Image (cartoon, coloured by chain):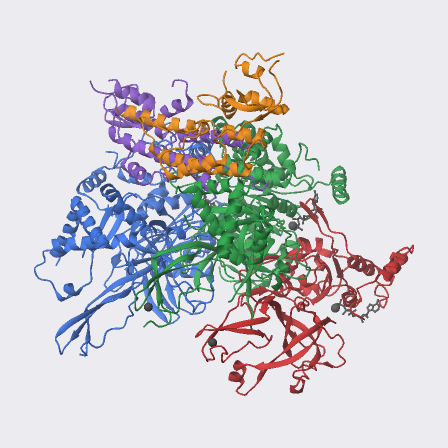
Amino acid sequence: AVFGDRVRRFQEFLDTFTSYRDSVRSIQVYNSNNANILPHRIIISLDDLREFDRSFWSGILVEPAYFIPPAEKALTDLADSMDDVPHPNASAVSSRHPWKLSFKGSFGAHALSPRTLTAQHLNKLVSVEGIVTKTSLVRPKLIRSVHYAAKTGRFHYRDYTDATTTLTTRIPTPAIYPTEDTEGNKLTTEYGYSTFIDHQRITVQEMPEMAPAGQLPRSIDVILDDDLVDKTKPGDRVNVVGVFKSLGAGGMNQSNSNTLIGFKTLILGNTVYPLARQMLTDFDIRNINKLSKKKDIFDILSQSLAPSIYGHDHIKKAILLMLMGGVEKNLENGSHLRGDINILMVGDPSTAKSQLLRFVLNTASLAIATTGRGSSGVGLTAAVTTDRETGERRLEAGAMVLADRGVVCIDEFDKMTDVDRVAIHEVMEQQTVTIAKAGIHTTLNARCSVIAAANPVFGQYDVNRDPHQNIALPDSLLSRFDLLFVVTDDINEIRDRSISEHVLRTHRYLPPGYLEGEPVRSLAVGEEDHVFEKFNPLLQAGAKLAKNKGNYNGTEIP
Amino acid sequence: GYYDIDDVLADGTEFPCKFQYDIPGLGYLENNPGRPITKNTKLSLPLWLARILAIVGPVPFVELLPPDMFSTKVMNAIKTDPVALDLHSINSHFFSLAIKWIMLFSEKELANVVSELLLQRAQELNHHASSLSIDLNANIATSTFLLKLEEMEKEIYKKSHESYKDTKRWMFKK
Amino acid sequence: MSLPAHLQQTFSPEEIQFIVENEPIKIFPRITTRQKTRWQLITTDDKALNNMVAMRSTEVVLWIALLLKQQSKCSIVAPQWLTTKELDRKIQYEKTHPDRFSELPWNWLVLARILFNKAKDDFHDPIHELRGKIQDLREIRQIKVLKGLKYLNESHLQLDNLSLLEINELRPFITEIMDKLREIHTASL
Amino acid sequence: SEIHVRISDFPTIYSLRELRESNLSSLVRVTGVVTRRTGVFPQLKYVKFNCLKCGSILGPFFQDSNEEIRISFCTNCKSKGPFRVNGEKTVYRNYQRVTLQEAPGTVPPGRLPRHREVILLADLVDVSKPGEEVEVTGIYKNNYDGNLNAKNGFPVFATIIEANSIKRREGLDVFSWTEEEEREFRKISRDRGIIDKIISSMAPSIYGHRDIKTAVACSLFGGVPKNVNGKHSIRGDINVLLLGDPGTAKSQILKYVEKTAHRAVFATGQGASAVGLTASVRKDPITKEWTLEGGALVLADKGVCLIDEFDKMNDQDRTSIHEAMEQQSISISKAGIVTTLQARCSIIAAANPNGGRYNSTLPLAQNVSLTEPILSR
Amino acid sequence: DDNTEIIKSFKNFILEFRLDSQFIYRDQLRNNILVKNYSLTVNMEHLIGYNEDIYKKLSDEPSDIIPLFETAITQVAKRISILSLPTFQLILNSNANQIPLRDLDSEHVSKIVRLSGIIISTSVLSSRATYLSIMCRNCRHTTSITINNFNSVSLPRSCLNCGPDPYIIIHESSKFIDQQFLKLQEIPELVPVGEMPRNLTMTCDRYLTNKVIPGTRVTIVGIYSIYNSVAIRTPYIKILGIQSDVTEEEEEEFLQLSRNPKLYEILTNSIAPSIFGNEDIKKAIVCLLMGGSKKILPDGMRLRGDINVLLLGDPGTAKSQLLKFVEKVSPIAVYTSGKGSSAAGLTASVQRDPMTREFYLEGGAMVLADGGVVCIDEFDKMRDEDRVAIHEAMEQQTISIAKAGITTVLNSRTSVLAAANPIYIDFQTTILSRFDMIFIVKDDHNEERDISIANHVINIHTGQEENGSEISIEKMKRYITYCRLKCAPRLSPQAAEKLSSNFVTIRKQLLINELESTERSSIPITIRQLEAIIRITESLAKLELSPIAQERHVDEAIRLFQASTMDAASQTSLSEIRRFEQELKRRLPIGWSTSYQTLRREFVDTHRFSQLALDKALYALEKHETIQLRHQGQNIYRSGV
Ligand SMILES: Nc1ncnc2c1ncn2[C@@H]1O[C@H](COP(=O)(O)OP(=O)(O)OP(=O)(O)O)[C@@H](O)[C@H]1O
Ligand SMILES: Nc1ncnc2c1ncn2[C@@H]1O[C@H](COP(=O)(O)OP(=O)(O)OP(=O)(O)O)[C@@H](O)[C@H]1O
Ligand SMILES: Nc1ncnc2c1ncn2[C@@H]1O[C@H](COP(=O)(O)OP(=O)(O)OP(=O)(O)O)[C@@H](O)[C@H]1O
Ligand SMILES: [Mg+2]
Ligand SMILES: [Mg+2]
Ligand SMILES: [Mg+2]
Ligand SMILES: [Zn+2]
Ligand SMILES: [Zn+2]
């Protein structure tokens, strides 16, 4: 009765807005032509539904369990009627593939965070924003089994149900395959014609900034099924929309005796909104050629990177040269001539070494700033690990291995321990790492480029001594670095004023938006000043001196 | 009116603009002195200048682009759930600027939304204003909502709270 | 300025009491003013005061009645509305109709407090019962007022038979909200 | 409503080694040292069961402390069906369990000590704490335990002592004084040279080292801790470091002050560790929740902590005492039991100079390996 | 019958109580309903006064009577709010004699008791049940059962055929309420000597959740009940009212205080009133307490605003006393001994949850100190790995431990006050450069000074203006909270130019200092030190609530920095190290080892090279693998060219 009325209402709503019908038709046509596969899903905007009918909008927002399934059935009926497949297949006929729904638009007080989710928001549609910390393995889930009875020559089927698969509760169906027909004939399971869907459980953690002072972060579990199975990885920021639910007996059954613990609550995900390379167009290639023809482009590219920094122009040139690397030769004898440049910086304190590292990190396609001083997190080189109790061996890749065909920006190279020194020597010399520990034998490529900074041993660079003396690494390590740069902090009055003013500017620079200087606090997922840069005294600064050739008076805008 | 601090401040907000003329000597308007202002160039101007430039020109000097506080996102947010919307973050003078916008462009679509939002917010404003305290021995929600009040709403709330408090004090005075 | 900030475009409860006390009330005098000096007030009639006999009911302004009660020279006659039976009848009337307001006197809140404080032994009914009935009436009126605030518009509003104290309570909020809505509507045209 | 009767002086005294089957269900007096203790819990004193088939409610019973009440047949419905505990109206009693172990001295040469479990009912809980020597008079009971039978392989019964009275181990306490004695002390204090007599009367068996006697007497008597508006804290304890040639009557004086001091703990530099000086974590057999033990410094609060062969202690252990020396508190973080413990005790330490002898020419800095901070303290 | 009578009694109590002229509870209920607060707070004194029998019944069997009180409250609320809502919650206030936590025993089972303690841990909100919809597996019979939190419910075992436990819960038509578990520890004062603090589990529901945090003294009114986990039961408390020791009048008082013309001097006086001298350290500690205004940039590079200080002097200087006072005064503070704790104690450590066996992250002292101040003592004894961990933590204020099964990160916005023993390099000048301010405390041997300190200490022992020259800890703490949460001042353009000129003058001052021709000055100043000079002026501005920092703050900050860091940094040699290294290399052939003590005798005792030049050269040589340290550095072995 009510189910039919709601199905009819959603059918009328879909008829009114032709965009969703067009989207369904487009998905179906793309699937048919490509016979890589578009999922059966449609994204609706809550604003349009609110405009069309307030009752249905409020029902979806407050009573999703009773209002969502009718919408899914209406969409499935529309798709089936619109379908024009002439000849289906045994896989398609028996497949349990209804059409799912996802929601976009503006939420009211339902746009919450993992900390704000309390018991008053249960059985309601919510939008949770946070950070992924855990990601369980992808596993298949049984939702339909088709059997064959040879004697009667008929195909039977049976449907299963679980608390994490349907918004509306039903009697649990144990995963026991029927073995005999009602008439008594023996059945044989047809595995190829059954239906299995994927299943993944992830845990979303509150964003650290929003966490109240002196409070640990709170997390909420999320369940994703079918197409939304492999879309997030740990550490990513997501905005998951789903229905908050409570599962299990929660100690209410007489078997349990705690009588104090509460029920288990999760979210049934409906959609996930996330929170390298740029495809070159036809005229971008023309632009790059135009710049290439200009017989001054090397200086332009060199000084475009890190324009703020004063001096050290040769370092910028060498850093660009490193970024673009050199051809790598593979001889027929298996010999491998290295074709990746390496750079090491050594100098007194406060010479923008970290600034140069940051700029190469920002401009480099790949980079990992794993400092050499106790690199907690990702190790500098690969090293197997085992669990404390289960002893689960596993090869954990280090920074060097995670930069294949890229760059690794080590920091504070002078703080390395003997283990790291020995590992790095082999890594650079051979360009590959072969692990032969804990019964694990494997080879992992490490072709990359290394840039590192290293302060002196006495805290200040001595000119009278060789660079190999001001640094305390053996010749084996230093020889691997193709180019070694020694930089000293020189004091010049004009330079001092320039640096002072440039640093001062930022402090008085403010977060524009609220009373200047006071207590300081994506729209879509699917998705010629462009090339050149207008001069900015605040940022570039020294870049003008670069084209002026060390002349402050020079006003040659570069 | 003329001598009204709240009215004066509201006119001081920055609205987007698009110059469609080529005027020299107006460099200081954009960001630098002594540089002619090209045409078809976007810049941010205070309202007290943008309004006059738009009205006075055959062809106005300026063409006011759609502001950022009246975009479709804000309209949808207002229509969805007026009470929980935080107007203070959007703009501290939302209602005065809105009224000025409707008067300037005489748009009959924003008026309905603004009126409904004001009515719905006033319901909760009165709900919170009438809830006083009792010292029986001899607020968290109130503070949470109070931080989301525009300047005009804050003034109305203060006046209503003072009236209610005075009446209660007189009524229960010994 | 010449007038405080809170007294602009509204009233104060003390002024409301001042207004309420300007009305007549019936009292039982305890002296014999009638002859066989004398009052010559200018704002109020002085004939009644000059002609009063003990235990014989007469009419005088509420302010003068309270002044006499201060010296214990008269006994105030509690109005007919204040009695319990009338209060139960009015409560039932309010409950029966969830849309209209009762028809109590406009000064049914100020007079109640003034009499409950100054004259606590003149009533013919228990004081606590009267206080409870008045509280119930006030609560029902508050509910109805809250429900009726959802119909503010830019044209006008009607609140038949609403006491002066409640109107004074609601004057700032209603007036300001209606003014803002009217300004928006006028700008729209 | 109940006044328990406790027997004080049982003539027959037994030990944890000589208890046999003949002593079952009889009054026995044993001596031992407490090495374990559990929290205080309420235990049912009169239970009232009910049925599940008919729902009938059984009458009152008495709950023995060692075995739980078992019913295998009803009386109202007279069926062997399941049962349950009901009758929310009940009267409870306190219940605690401690592990009593034989005194190390009493144990014959190099034999394993024998331990039993003692059950303390209402009015007896929190009457003793770990590390005490006590005498327990109670009923030596036994009961059937399935786990023991399954493990050993023979019909063996668990045994436990239901305590009836606990006493500490002349009289009851020498430190306790009477009103009559308090008058004697005032008379003695009036002596003109009482201080000299106190110093002389301290370690008389040792001839010389009057400076040692003065310092140690001052440490024993102690100071007056002071606090200023809760903003400034001044320690009242006095710390004395003893340093000199090998044979000088150093350890013997510490042994003497151990006896004389009210609450004293004796630890040697070699035989000590930070875990044993701060606290140790155990698992409660009842609640299965991790608790925290007391350390050597904690056990000697408001007393004296004597350390012998101080120079021999390792650096980490010597750092563990820095906190107690000046901060007068020890901080612990183990097994999510982060808390701060109170340790206000004076420390008397004895050591020999580095190299085995004190070179009078060189200063105290090089003579002993202790760092400048601790030396200053 | 009886239940209806009790409900009517409660209704009459609520509707009839009145002290002078105002119906307290009626008006309170109306006000609470208006703001969507479904609760009622009742003072037990009023209940006793109105009718003693009602209180007698309430205290006799609270678990049975309290739900009826909630029902009556709900009925009255519906009568008062709806013209002819969830079950309301009852909160109780009482003034009965407090029962010590350690003294709770079986005698107080199922009785209302009042106690006090300190919260040590709080859980995350659970979801208890209040109205369950149940359907039978076989015959599919729909039914509903209501549940009340108080115990003196489980799914039916017999269907209302169907076997045991035939009912399942329909979760789409049920209602739930919040629950939380807290732990209460007895007050330190009441703990008997030689014993240990005892803990007690507690439970709160609905509007009593998220009302306290660990480390807050609280007073609890609740039911002492027992829940089954020989025949023993686990005690616990059911909370009914929370009153923790933690407006406009105080704003007026604070504003008047800020108007005092010597606010800076009084605040510097309140810092350690009991410690004599060390005025510069006192001012630096004041600046650290107030801190610096936060800076955030749209690009992503947000500058630090907090302040850290280093106290490095000889023993007997009251550094620890200063740290203790700083810990006590600040609203949020953690006092930690460097050697007492470890890497786990500070920053954070990755551990595993025993109950669930999942790798999780637990914060250290800095995490627990987020938004406050951490006073680290004995910086020297702390291990080098912990020191570098602290280096990173102060560098980014976000301890980055996100690996090993999880990828979670925590914020550590904190101010570090470090007291370190004298160096007499492990204490390399780099970590010092990280510190904003460096102080070397040295008492000068002036007879007047010695007598003054002696008199001060004797006055301490034999022993409070607080009349315009000092303020107690409570007022100062509230002051710090107000100033840190309200005002975030910023410097001024003229002050900015003046400070730039000041740095120029400092560089020129070194230029004057370097009268030497060949010798090179170590450092005039670093850019990090320049940033350090700023953010203390904002501290002074926030101290006085000044929206813009004027030149006065600039000169004050300049003097404070000059009196601490430049002199301490200043408080040839490399060429000598070259000769020492050459001699050591020449003396020892390859493979020949000589005792480090023997080398010290050869050179240090001979005085040809000072000891500070021995360790430096030895470290420089060892780090290059040319030499090796053996026997804890007591034997030196050459290992190549
Ligand atoms: N050429 C330069 N132009 C502008 N600023 C500079 C230049 N060289 C150094 N700086 C300033 O030096 C400051 C210090 O930079 P950074 O902390 O990265 O120094 P570092 O020498 O790499 O440090 P460390 O000695 O600790 O390894 C930066 O704020 C930058 O402003
Ligand atoms: N002044 C003295 N009078 C009496 N006996 C003394 C005296 N000095 C030393 N002795 C005796 O010297 C012996 C030395 O043993 P004791 O336990 O006293 O310390 P120790 O082993 O010499 O000390 P250390 O730990 O410094 O090696 C003891 O028997 C003590 O009786
Ligand atoms: N001016 C002073 N007024 C009072 N006490 C002072 C003063 N200067 C030093 N002190 C001393 O400081 C002591 C407490 O601080 P403490 O000496 O432990 O600090 P510290 O020097 O850091 O210690 P250590 O270096 O030994 O670890 C008090 O006992 C005390 O009398
Ligand atoms: Mg650096
Ligand atoms: Mg000895
Ligand atoms: Mg100290
Ligand atoms: Zn039975
Ligand atoms: Zn059934």
Q: Nearer the viewer, residue E423 or C130?
A: C130
Choose top left, top right, bottom left or bottom right for residue E408.
bottom left
Output the letter for the chain in red. Answer: D
- The one nearer the camera, E95 or A334, is E95
x and y, in percent, of residue E281 in the image: 62, 40
Q: Quadrant of the C terminus of chain C?
A: top left
When asked about the image quadrant of residue E482, the answer is top right
Q: Position of residue A30 (x, y in %)?
A: 14, 53
Q: Residue at x 25, y 28 (%)?
A: B108
Residue C121 location, x and y as percent? 59, 32
Q: Is residue A496 left or right of residue D252?
A: left
Colour applied to chain B:
purple
Q: Going by the image, does E477 lie left or right of E133?
A: right
Vertical side of D130 occupied by E372: above or below: above
Q: Colour of chain A?
A: blue
| Residue A172 in view (yes/no) | yes
Chain E, hue in figure: green
**Chain that is coloured orange in the picture:** C
Indicate the quadrant where residue A313 lies.
top left
